[PDB]
Image (cartoon, coloured by chain):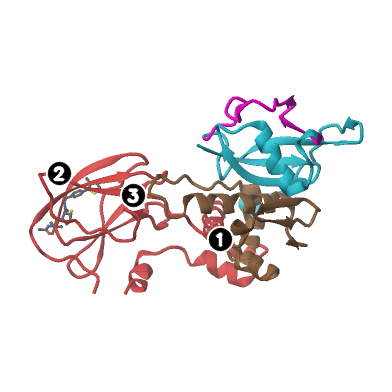
Amino acid sequence: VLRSVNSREPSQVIFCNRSPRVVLPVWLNFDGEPQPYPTLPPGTGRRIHSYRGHLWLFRDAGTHDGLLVNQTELFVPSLNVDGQPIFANITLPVYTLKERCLQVVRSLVKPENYRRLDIVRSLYEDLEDHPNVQKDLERLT
Amino acid sequence: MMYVKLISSDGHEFIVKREHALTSGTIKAMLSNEVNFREIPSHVLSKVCMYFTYKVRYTNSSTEIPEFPIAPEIALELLMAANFLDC
Amino acid sequence: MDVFLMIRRHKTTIFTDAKESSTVFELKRIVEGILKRPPDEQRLYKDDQLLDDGKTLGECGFTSQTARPQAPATVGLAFRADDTFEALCIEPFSSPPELPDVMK
Ligand SMILES: CC(=O)N[C@H](C(=O)N1C[C@H](O)[C@H](F)[C@H]1C(=O)NCc1ccc(-c2scnc2C)cc1)C(C)(C)C
């Protein structure tokens, strides 16, 4: 279902990382497989050549936490008007306080020790269920 | 402007807008003008109140969003309280 | 520009916002509505300094980039009972426990 269209029609884009995280762009190829591309440090940008009808999403390169692009999940390059590139603003979402707490804890405790923590079993499951690109694709289908 | 009182386990009394507090479905229920929390110390409940302010200021804003900060000392207790309050 | 504050006296803390251009007196009006005490029975503070009614919050150092939603600035509050003002007193928050072994 979710896959780039093989249009072969170029589209110039700016990836602009307005987050404090190191960013990993992910191109969904013609069979729907996620393909990683080089990372962007916080506050940096890249001018890149993509194509009309292609699908991208964006992640934290180290924890795989999900990020937003022009306020939403998926970004699809469109027609360039007047030879101007399409802007792709990558930002932090307003995470729930719960999901933020999980991020920090995951970054402090090694996965082998989640169980040694003093919390209810369903929070152990919430910690072990770290963000994953495959799951989010299944969700968004 | 309506306000409500949220009270920590150690007696600290925090006073916030009614609109902000209703971010939590759990608090919405405990009202439908004061609420006592017997498990939540003030060093956690203050951070919860700051999250309300943060969420309402940055929800659906096209400006850049800063990270909501959490000290390692308070991360576990805060996790438990956010799970309970559903925020 | 909005500034975000905690107004604190004893074990009371108020979360609210105000304009950088608004006055100290106008902030007491806000307290009056919540705690039912008129401005003439209130003193406000930045740390140990008493604040003048006519001055703006910006003049007194509360700016939009220091007084943020996720990290608001603190403003001290003290009441008058009868003739004289109480001393400014703010109870600290609780202490976090020690970090567990697995977080060190
Ligand atoms: C005709 C077609 O669809 N070509 C694809 C293509 O050229 N793509 C797929 C995406 O549209 C992507 F944009 C483009 C591509 O790979 N462009 C080169 C490229 C290289 C590095 C980067 C990035 S991402 C973060 N930093 C950089 C330098 C972005 C684009 C193939 C070669 C991967 C099949």
From the rendered image, report the letter of the chain displayed in brown: B
Q: Any magenta on residue C48?
A: yes
* Of residues B19 and A111, the one drawn nearer to the viewer in this rendering: B19
- Res A52 → quadrant: bottom left
Please give the residue where the numbered disc 3 appears in the rendered image: A90
Callout 2 environment at 10 Å: few (<14), some (14 to 19), or many (20+)?
Answer: few
Residue, disc 2: A84
Q: Is mark 3 within 8 Å of ligand 1?
A: no
Q: Colour of chain C?
A: cyan
> Could you tell me how far apart the alpha carbons at marks 2 and 1 are, in whole angstroms?
40 Å
Q: Which chain is red?
A: A
Q: Which residues are magenta?
A: C41-64
- The residue positioned 22% from the left and 59% from the top of the image is A76
Front residue of C18/A100: it is C18
Along the horizontal axis of the image, is A104 left or right of C6? left
**Left or right position of A14 against A123:** left
Q: Is residue C79 left or right of residue A15?
A: right
Q: Residues within 10 Å of mark 1 (few under 14, many from 20)?
A: some
Of callouts 3 and 2, which one flags the residue occurring earlier in the amino acid sequence?
2
Q: Nearer the viewer, residue C40 or B56?
A: C40
Q: Which amino acid is tagged 3?
A: Ile
Which amino acid, mark 2?
A: Gln
**Is any part of residue C97 visible from this angle?**
no
Quarter of the picture holding the C terminus of chain A: bottom left
